Image (cartoon, rainbow, N blue to C red; front, side, top):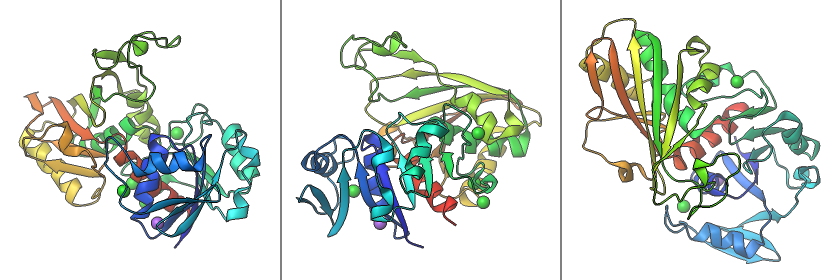
Length: 331
Ligand SMILES: [Cl-]
Ligand SMILES: [Cl-]
Ligand SMILES: [Cl-]
Ligand SMILES: [Cl-]
Ligand code: NA
């Protein structure tokens, strides 16, 4: 009904999740933790290069934050066991620091008073992952879950539809992805990912992403049938997937369009979108759907070998689904 949420990590996702929460009445952010002074969090919230100025009022009082007349407890604990979430009545924690993606590390929020935790990234251990449009129904009361990755949220719903209707024998996917915080402005160090340390604005950078393989986990029926890679390009936000699949049942492109459009207007409304316009990436900046099929962009070699294209706002879509998952596990 009215779920109290605590955000750990006020980075890109933390902040977009925060903004999306203002527009929902069933969820309230009541606390934020990060290694930042309240006055600086206020700044990061008020102004955003990609999504413009915060629609609302934000002031600082007594080292805490006041957003639209509500107190938000601001803390700067490095170790999550000290967060004392129960003091501000937190039901669920959105773990968004990118550092606690295992059960033992995330479990600390529960030790600190929170009832459940939602990792805003794919889990490094086998913490179960949930993707709206793919397997929310599979949630089974676990107290710690993952909302997977932004790319998986784009791919899973589309793949599910395609597979349910025509059967995916095998597929390879590519995502042309926007630049992110892990990259560098100019050629710099990235010991675990050499290419990733190259100047982001000057290059097309190949990168790895198990996101395609991870679909196998949220959609068991596709386990071992998909995999892929990514190219990081110089745009600040919004990415796109290029799924190339081989189908069991023959289907004309017109039939595929109809299948997706049906899903978008029906069962997967709000998750999977459909467009026939001449769109470009900026047209999805701010998009809430996690996957928006681009009918005109895709191409079919034949009734059984097709290349499908779907857009996604890697910050906004995912952030909204984090909230959707929080709401879902709180039923
Ligand atoms: Cl806003
Ligand atoms: Cl999983
Ligand atoms: Cl679902
Ligand atoms: Cl469901
Ligand atoms: Na709210």
